[PDB]
Amino acid sequence: HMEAVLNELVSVEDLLKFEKKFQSEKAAGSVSKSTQFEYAWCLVRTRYNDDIRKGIVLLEELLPKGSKEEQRDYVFYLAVGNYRLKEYEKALKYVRGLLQTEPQNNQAKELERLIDKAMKKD
């Protein structure tokens, strides 16, 4: 419970920090891929559905711009975002594709197990 409390307060701090940085950089010119990512990452972990959807959209904008390494990461967080929105089919499509490119990624494998467990129980 305390761990969950720590996690929730940190997520708020994170979101506010990167929202400011993203909006600041946006007004001054092109936003860096790093800042867009950090913000999208916080967004997909938010308690609000509109933030999660915004995070998913930002990650999708980053997809055609990133390196092979970065794109694999974007797909992972796209799976996480969709999972938290209960869009299991979309989440699974991402994860399964990620497992084909990164076989040794057990975090992706654990996410697929979590999605499958969630469909069975809930």
Image (cartoon, rainbow, N blue to C red):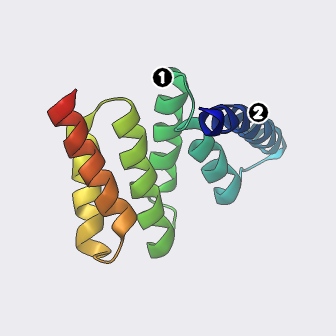
Tell me whether circle 1 and circle 2 mark residues in contact (CB < 8 Å). Answer: no
Where is the N terminus found, in terms of image quarters? top right
Tell me, for residue 16, which label it has, or none: 2
Judge left or right: residue 2 versus residue 107: right
**Mark 2 is on which residue type?**
Leu
Judge left or right: residue 120 versus residue 20: left
Q: In the depicted view, which residue is nearer to us: 70 or 99? A: 99
- For mark 1, what is the residue? 49
Question: Which residue: 35% across, 68% down?
Answer: 106
Q: Position of residue 76 (x, y in %)?
A: 41, 56
Judge left or right: residue 99 versus residue 15: left
* Camera sees residue 62: yes
Task: Determine whether the residue tagged by mark 2 lies in a helix, strand or loop.
Answer: helix
Judge left or right: residue 88 versus residue 7: left
Question: Which residue: 44% across, 74% down?
Answer: 68
Circle 1 crowding by C-alpha within 10 Å: few under 14, some 14–19, many from 20: some
Q: Earlier in the sequence, mark 1 or mark 2?
A: 2
Q: Position of residue 122 (x, y in %)?
A: 22, 26
Q: In this view, does 103 lie above or below 80?
A: below
Q: In the depicted view, which residue is nearer to us: 85 or 31? A: 85
Circle 2 crowding by C-alpha within 10 Å: few under 14, some 14–19, many from 20: some
Task: Determine whether the residue tagged by mark 1 lies in a helix, strand or loop.
Answer: helix
Q: Position of residue 95 (x, y in %)?
A: 28, 56
Mark-to-mark CA distance, 1 and 2? 16 Å
Q: Position of residue 92 (x, y in %)?
A: 23, 48
Question: Which residue: 36% across, 48% down?
Answer: 79
The number of discs equals: 2
Q: In this view, does 66 lie above or below 102?
A: above
* Camera sees residue 67: no
Q: In this view, does 73 lie above or below 3?
A: below
Q: In the depicted view, which residue is nearer to us: 50 or 86? A: 86
